[PDB]
Image (cartoon, grey):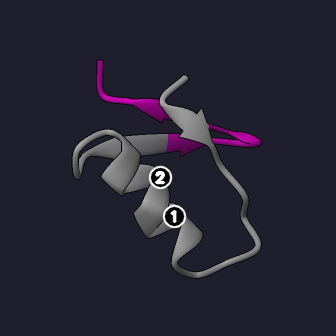
């Protein structure tokens, strides 16, 4: 993964993007990168 994902916060999804250097993809409890 890139890091974790939590569908609680409106700005977590943005934070999962920032983990992948701007361009991530959240897949349930995990945040994964576009790589």
Question: Dot 1 corresponds to which residue?
Answer: 13
Please state, as top left, top right, bottom left or bottom right, where the C terminus lies in the image.
top left
* Crowdedness near tag 1: few (<14), some (14–19) or many (≥20) residues, C-alpha within 10 Å: some
Please state, as top left, top right, bottom left or bottom right, where the N terminus lies in the image.
top right
Q: Secondary structure at mark 2?
A: helix
Cα–Cα gap, marks 1 and 2: 5 Å
Which residue does the image show at 56% across and 36% down from the upper left?
Answer: 3
x and y, in percent, of residue 17 in the image? 36, 53
- 1 horizontally vs 5: left or right: left
Report the predominant secondary structure element of the magenta stretch: strand
What is the tally of numbered marks visible in this picture? 2
Question: Dot 2 corresponds to which residue?
Answer: 16
Query: Do callouts 1 and 2 mark residues in contact (Cβ within 8 Å)?
Result: yes
- 31 within the magenta span: yes
Answer above or below: position of 7 versus 9.
Answer: above
The residue lying furthest to the left in this view is: 22
x and y, in percent, of residue 18 in the image? 33, 54
- 17 horizontally vs 15: left or right: left
Which residue does the image show at 45% across and 62% down from the upper left?
Answer: 15
The residue lying furthest to the top in this view is: 35
Q: Which residues are magenta?
A: 26-35
Answer above or below: position of 14 versus 21.
Answer: below
Which residue does the image show at 76% across and 42% down from the upper left?
Answer: 29
Which residue does the image show at 67% across and 78% down from the upper left?
Answer: 9
């Amino acid at each position: 993964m890139c890091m974790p994902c939590f569908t609680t916060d409106p700005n977590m999804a943005k934070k999962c993007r920032d983990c992948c250097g701007g361009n991530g993809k959240c897949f349930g409890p995990q945040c994964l990168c576009n790589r």
